[PDB]
Image (cartoon, rainbow, N blue to C red; front, side, top):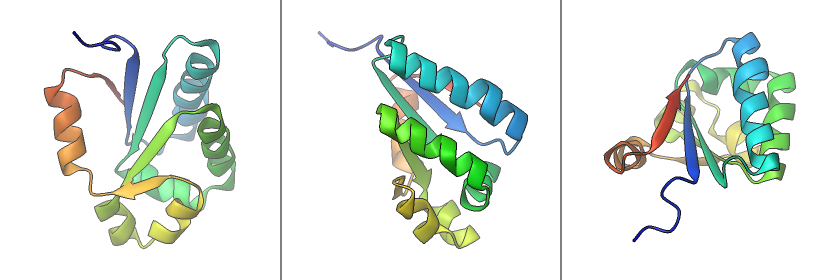
Length: 116
């Protein structure tokens, strides 16, 4: 059946704790992608994290490196619109879309999801 069933990691990134963002989340995602530990890595920006990414240039630098490595990053469009940052987030190369259906599907499909 499925040809990639154990090859994708999803991270639900809600935290705005910079220590955890830099030293756990970005470091593991980048190394995983670059070394082939995970063939596919998707990061969902939803919650306090959306404000952090919009406002913090050091975090933006990490976002750009992650995107360059082939990690996909999508942000909750409701959050982006409520916080007034959709243009900023889109301009970083992050996909902005309504996230309710996607998250539901990821969970229903039995994805491996680290909720940070």
